[PDB]
Length: 51
Length: 49
Image (cartoon, rainbow over all chains, first blue to last red):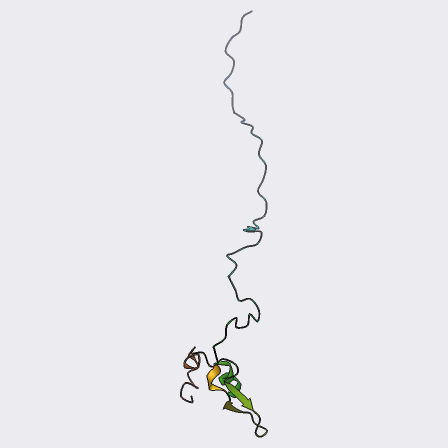
C-alpha cells in the first residue's frame, strides 16, 4: 500500500512564454544628423569706410 | 563680368555703366573702397584690375 518507483519518464517538456520580433525600421532620430550652421539671408555689410 | 567685378569691391567703387548694348564697368569713386582684396579670389579678374 506504499508508494513505489514507476517507469522512467520517456520525455521532458519545458514551457516558457515568449513574444516575437517586429520589422526593422531603425528610426534613428526625431530631427536627425548634425544639422549644419548656415548663412542668414542677405545679411548686408554693417560697416563702411571713411570718405 | 562687369557685375562680378562690381561685387568684388565695396559697392560704390565700380559703377557699371551701359555705354552700348553691352555693359561696361567703370571706376566711379575709388575712395569708397575698403581693402578686402576679394578680386584676388576671382582667378580671372585679378589680372584685369
